Image (cartoon, rainbow, N blue to C red; front, side, top):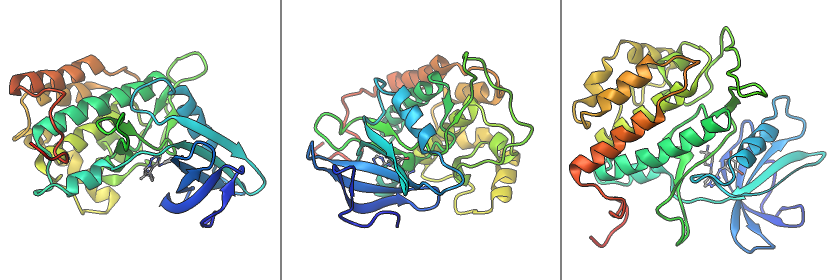
Length: 293
Ligand SMILES: CC1(N)CCN(Cc2ccn3ncnc(Nc4cc(O)cc(Br)c4)c23)CC1
């Protein structure tokens, strides 16, 4: 570990325990000695050849003001490490789904989370970045009375700017080795093609099927190439057998997109809102992990 327990960063953030990472950087839960709340602290070695924290802080700062984004607390660089401190969130959607009796969320919870996640994807795209690792463990519910029903997008370590300085789409590289988690990667990512906005929406599509059905066909198939070949040959409409019928428009829309084209986020938002309206799903409903009725 880069930092041991009780290490104090900038005489303010006291490391409590490691909560993630290890390879590119490490993430800790820390005590803010000024404000007295716990926070998340990510560190990366100053000697590391591939350093992402400067880009990760840049995305986090650009997103301040948007919903579904952690508050920026601080950042810095010294001779041993670079660091970023941000608001700490709670339970992630991978753990919440596995804690459900049959490993599935209800359609009520699935669709409401889908709307929140779509909002966060449109937000990162609006500031010129792709997330590239949209997955349930990168979405966490709040941990406060003011946030416990809000879902947050986490971790910009694998993000990439898809625009130049003037808002134009950058050229795609001729090959781009995909970095994201195998289970939720799009077929385009599996082909090592430059990712676009549509590839983050493919990851959302797979997450929502997994939430409502409880599994994907390639779950626990670990080999990258084999998973991509299954997805390439799999009839995606078969994934929609027990999903709301309007998801066929979502699938058809994202299947029509290419690297360059801006998605129709409103079309996808309507798929979720219309699916909820038809089933009488309201925003005030308890999420599955909430008790008392
Ligand atoms: C599984 C994952 N990808 C995402 C979850 N973190 C652990 C975790 C648990 C609760 N929270 N709240 C805020 N930020 C977190 N991570 C975080 C990620 C960053 O990239 C930068 C910073 Br600062 C914190 C985090 C481990 C790496």
